[PDB]
Image: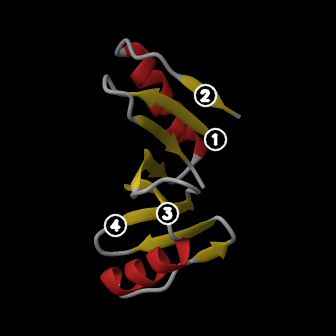
Amino acid sequence: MSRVQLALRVPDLEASIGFYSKLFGTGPAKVRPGYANFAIAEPPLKLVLIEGAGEDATRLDHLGVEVEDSAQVGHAARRLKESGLATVEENDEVWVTGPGGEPWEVYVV
């Protein structure tokens, strides 16, 4: 089991927290200056809002797949490299980039 992560760079974190609390009917799980996390049950989603100074509009920061443990990250890392994709792991996460530049990370919290 896993869930997608969607990390957005937003020009107004406070307004965005308010909007997403209403959209998904739940408050943020974690709130800091500069970022907020929502753990949504349905639809399964990890939503990250990152404050972006002098971005005129919301844009994609990165995308992800949130998995249950480090072994799942390792499995994904091995699989993506096998399939010919350039990757970088961190010691848990592995990063790949799509052809138009969109970055993905498979990670465990």
Q: Residues within 10 Å of mark 4 (few under 14, many from 20)?
A: few
| Residues at discs 3 and 4 in contact (Cβ within 8 Å) | no
Q: Amino acid at mark 2?
A: Glu
Give the mark nearer the N terminus: 3 vs 1: 3
Q: Name the residue that disc number 1 marks.
A: 92
Give the mark nearer the N terminus: 3 vs 2: 3
The residues tagged by marks 4 and 2 sit, at their Cα atoms, a distance apart of 25 Å
Task: Identify whether 45 is placed above or below 61.
Answer: below
Q: Which mark is residue 11?
A: 3
Q: Name the residue that disc number 4 marks.
A: 44
What residue is rendered at 51% in x and 64% in y? Answer: 49
Q: Residues within 10 Å of mark 3 (few under 14, many from 20)?
A: some
Q: Which mark is residue 89?
A: 2
| Residues at discs 1 and 2 in contact (Cβ within 8 Å) | yes
Q: Nearer the viewer, residue 79 or 10?
A: 10
Give the mark nearer the N terminus: 1 vs 4: 4
